[PDB]
Image (cartoon, rainbow over all chains, first blue to last red; front, top):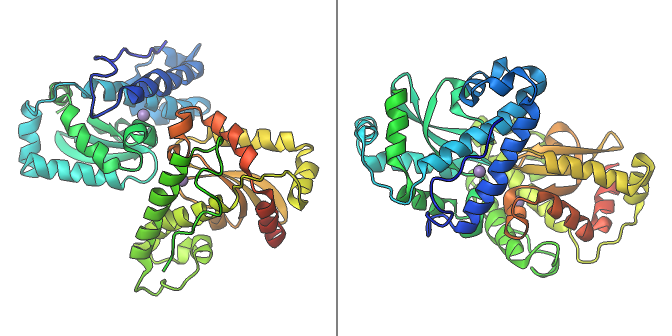
Length: 198
Length: 198
Ligand SMILES: [Mn+2]
Ligand SMILES: [Mn+2]
């Protein structure tokens, strides 16, 4: 069975960038619901012993009756699990991934400007991702709980821009949430995922 | 130009079903943003005097370069405009539309149960609608700001299930928001839109 992972930090560790109350709802309610529904779909099937990353990457091979729930609930579990691991109370812009971002975008600010533009223009619910595509870095968005793995791209950083991720503190001000996020990126984790994928 | 319509009631008129703070953000920020961006797209173009119902029903005829903004921001203006008008602090379950709902679904409760199931299973951002389709009533969902007019169905009642519509009071408990909504439906306005469409 899939399990709700513990947060790597206290619920208030990301203040004042993400509020404690949002971390509690987001993890204990939203993410938990995706795990519950994913397990209800795969329990007693071949997919109960398939890796989450493999079923997301190969969603087209998931049996038709199960595919929407694996896409939505499996995507929810995969995306939130990644999200908690790429946040940290002490974000420092260090690691090979920063050199390779600078190499691709010229400056870290040019990278952040593209990421923020894509995150702020995403219409409805979804995610903004930094991915590795055949050894090259790209920023992409996905709707709802869709994940770039399904399109053959490995995610190493994601921002959740579902309104539940930011509404209690920021309400409509998604751009202020985006600005806050740079203060709490776990670049140690992003670099680990990059070095494994590149 | 398109204009942000005034609410037909005080911002606190729908308490304790929808909180005043949500009415303020939802109307004064979210709806206003759709009006601003729709006007930025259409002002000074050959669409600057076209009605919004006509453009949404005929998105294919909207020029490719303006279509996403008309769909998303035009949808946002159309949808929220309808929404404010079908809420009321003085809801009474009577009218031709209520009689015809009871005739079609058997009971009003069976209608509400279907509507609630569609509203609570809608994945991501969107709306739940009561529509007229060739003189018959149907419940349909749309994603984001899409509208059933594009598919040739006239909307007479909509529930906004974007998270901004309910997160401040209800957080993840979308079903409690759906329960609250029945207490504030303007069945007189719904009946007007029904008589005009059936
Ligand atoms: Mn989320
Ligand atoms: Mn809305």
